[PDB]
Structure formats: C-alpha cells, structure tokens
Length: 150
Ligand SMILES: Nc1nc2c(nc(Br)n2[C@@H]2O[C@@H]3COP(=O)(O)O[C@H]3[C@H]2O)c(=O)[nH]1
Ligand SMILES: [Ca+2]
Ligand SMILES: [Ca+2]
Ligand SMILES: [Ca+2]
Ligand SMILES: [Ca+2]
Ligand code: NA
Image (cartoon, rainbow, N blue to C red):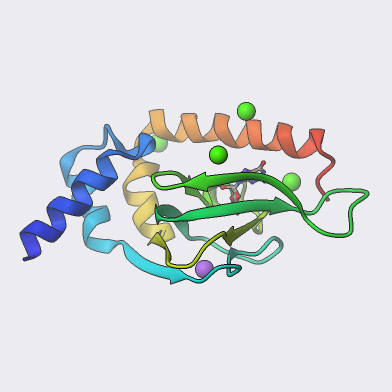
C-alpha cells in the first residue's frame, strides 16, 4: 500500500537526527523523491576524489569510512556507520570532490539516495540545519587535518 510504504519511510526518516524536526511537507518531499541503492560487501558507495552531489542515509547494514592519509599507502579506517546515520553532505557544504571512501561492510547494505535538489529544498532550506551541518563539516575538517589526510 502506498500509505503503508510512506508511513514506514516517515517513521524511519523521523529517526534520523538531522531530519527529526523537519516540517511535514519537507519530510514528504524526501519521502517522494528518495531512491534506494543496494550494495554488496566491499562496494564503494562513495570513492574519495570523485565528483558527487548525492546525500546518503544508511537504511540497512554497516559501512566503513576510509581515507588516504600521509605516510600510508592504503586508505586508513576512520570509523564505521550504522542504520540511521548519514554521509556525503561534505561535498555539498565544502563544494568539493568526495573526501573519503564509504564502503559497504556486509552484503545487502541499503542506502537512501537524496539528490542535490531534494537536499537543497528540504534540509538546505532551514538555517538551523545549515548552520549545524557547517559546524559538523568544520569538525570533519579538523579531524582531516589532525590525521594528515591527503
Ligand atoms: N572528510 C571526511 N569525511 C568524513 C569523515 N567522517 C565521515 Br562519516 N565522513 C563522510 O565521508 C564522506 C565522503 O564524501 P563527502 O566528502 O561528500 O562527505 C563525507 C562525510 O559525509 C571524516 O573524518 N572526514
Ligand atoms: Ca560509529
Ligand atoms: Ca538559509
Ligand atoms: Ca568529533
Ligand atoms: Ca580536505
Ligand atoms: Na554509490
């Protein structure tokens, strides 16, 4: 049922920190425009250095965050993320290429894929959320500098 589907997505999206206080009409816009992409173990959802403008919410499974850093020939493992966490906002906020890899850690990982326009018309319309994400990205920049990210 369309209604049952939309209710399931509404309940999930309201469990995401960043989205919990969105007006109904903006949550409905996300519900209407999100897409789902599925990944197998080891797949790169995001690859450092590539262009990208999608915002992702992890809906099922776990992902690894890895990043190239000075003194290491392979990207180093920074953290892992789980259901309800999000990623890919930094390319939009920093106006940059992707700055880390996001790798599926297991099979049947599912992410919600939110394009730039949808992001801009929902999350990006609320100054409190923009300022929050600006501060979060600033902390990511601090972390990048402290580990000597390439
Ligand atoms: N640069 C950077 N990015 C991090 C970090 N942790 C995460 Br989650 N991320 C996420 O990894 C994504 C890679 O694509 P992005 O640069 O668009 O956004 C990044 C962030 O959402 C981090 O320490 N540094
Ligand atoms: Ca974690
Ligand atoms: Ca604004
Ligand atoms: Ca921190
Ligand atoms: Ca950087
Ligand atoms: Na992808």
